Length: 48
Length: 48
Image 1 (cartoon, chains in turn brown, cyan):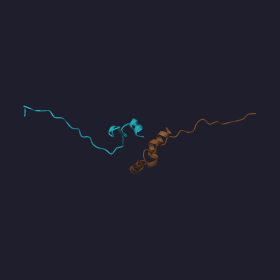
Image 2: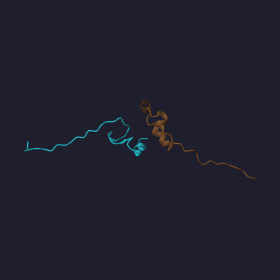
Image 3: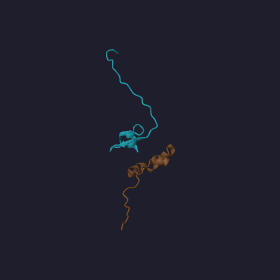
Image 4: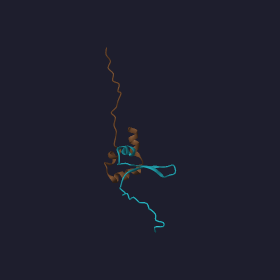
């Protein structure tokens, strides 16, 4: 008898351009987003 | 006058541009170093 088992070893590695994802390159959006701290850097570091 | 003639210095004028800068603040509160975010790819890495 043959028992088949799948054991995953990877997930797809995704890096998100936080600034472009949130603001789409708009100066007003970036100014309003800067009030949230350093969120984009935290996201980048976490994903990396 | 020719008795006490002196050679004076020169001043340099640099234009100010609207740019994103990564500023590093000293323990005394002074900006000791900065990064021009759009200047280089390493600078983009530092700013992101």
